[PDB]
Length: 376
Ligand SMILES: COC[C@@H](Oc1cc(C[C@@H]2C[S@@](=O)C[C@H](NCc3cccc(C(C)(C)C)c3)[C@H]2O)cc(F)c1N)C(F)(F)F
Image (tube, rainbow, N blue to C red; front, side):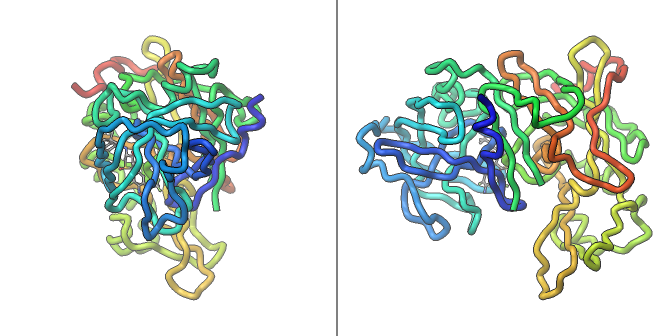
């Protein structure tokens, strides 16, 4: 019955993907950002310049105050509010209702995005990183505990944008080829291990621990591919060399300045493909996902009145490990198989197009000593 969940996601470029939910009795409708990088379910519950609607606890007969405060500091953005529980449903999701923890957001700073069209966030990761602490049961744990929904979900994020969140299973009509699985290293973030990196077929040749320093996570709430300082520098250097045929302001490589070309003349060919190899399911085995420039050059509306094609560099430097954000996930079907502690990747039905190249998930590869790639 997964067909009812196909295309249940919407979004705007650089502004996340959201699903429709209802909270309270009678049901109040809200759009909720889908975030595999956090574990709190939180909604605007007070007026805000960027909110067109919000959760009104006073109007819900099933609302229960937990009489505890809470705050969450993200990389960028934070909010604080009051904890409580209430009934929650997903109209274009499984046909169930659950009582879940909800953080009612009363104050925030750089959390809500002007024009994003979402009013809350659904953290889909594990209790370990929930605030105030791991005793606050995350939404998906409540869903699985209270219903017969199987303990997994999958995300098809498509390149204003749409996608699918299949709750409780895998919809085989949403991908082509085979699914390749990498272990979830530890259940807090969706942490994985990258074992090799190549750019246009050239190995970066770093200690693979550098790729996962201090962790690597799959995070739908983050837009960019984010890379640890040393890896970022090596990657940009290689990407610059490959595209040196053209000139870019260095504010572009910092993800600040956008670059434009005459509509339809974007020189895709001069930008390399990036291959990330992930730890596999059997001994000394891995697989790779290959990312095209159409993924890491994010389309942005022209600052000028011109109808050029403009882009921002969507790879940026991190001090908290690798983050495989939305631009990596786009064009792949990603299965969060919590039941079997693994994450699967397959080429998405809405895969990214290139004239002479194609995003891919390929294996098996042999890779020795993969355990040594994890950072401790
Ligand atoms: C520019 O934003 C676009 C972004 O909007 C937001 C998205 C988030 C979710 C964040 C995005 S970034 O902060 C990484 C983080 N995941 C890893 C992480 C890093 C630090 C702390 C935590 C804990 C929550 C576990 C404590 C988790 C993730 O959840 C928070 C926000 F405010 C905004 N606006 C959009 F629109 F989704 F693309």
